[PDB]
Amino acid sequence: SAKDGDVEGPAGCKKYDVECDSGECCQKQYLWYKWRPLDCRCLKSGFFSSKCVCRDV
């Protein structure tokens, strides 16, 4: 069985809520008890300096 933090791809890749290059995220990640893809989205929530990180897509 898989748990939170579990991802798919090469060892040492990126994870949920993490910066990356070329806006490319790991293969997949166990989110909400479901393996979904990741995308480096750039959005801010009432913050001053927005940031780009991987998110469920």
Image (cartoon, helix red, strand yellow):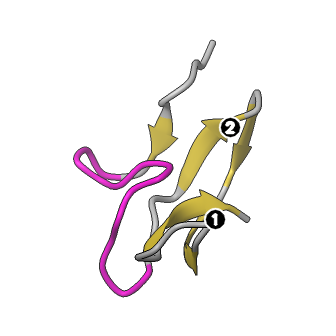
Decide whether the magenta segment is chiefly helix, strand or loop.
loop
**Image coords of residue 12 (percent x, y):** 22, 48
Image position of 51 (left or right of 11):
right
Image position of 11 (left or right of 6):
left
**Image coords of residue 21 (percent x, y):** 30, 79
Judge by depth and name the residue closer to the eye, 42 or 10. Answer: 42
Q: Quadrant of the N terminus?
A: top right
Tag 2 residue = 31
Tag 1 residue = 45
**Image coords of residue 9 (percent x, y):** 41, 51
Q: Residue at x 48, y 40 (%)?
A: 7
Residues shaded magenta:
10-23
Q: Residue at x 52, y 67 (%)?
A: 47
Choose top left, top right, bottom left or bottom right for residue 13: bottom left
Q: Residue at x 39, y 56 (%)?
A: 18
Circles 1 and 2: CB atoms closer than 8 Å: no
Judge by depth and name the residue closer to the eye, 34 or 10. Answer: 34
In 3D space, how far apart are the residues under numbered discs 1 and 2 (Cα atoms)? 21 Å
Q: Is residue 56 above or below residue 53?
A: above
Judge by depth and name the residue closer to the eye, 42 or 3. Answer: 42
Which of pointers 1 and 2 indicates the residue nearer the eye?
Answer: 1
Indicate yes or no whether the magenta region holds residue 15: yes
Whichever of callouts 1 and 2 sits on the residue coming sooner in the sequence is 2
* Residue type highlighted by circle 2: Leu
Q: Residue extending furthest left?
A: 12
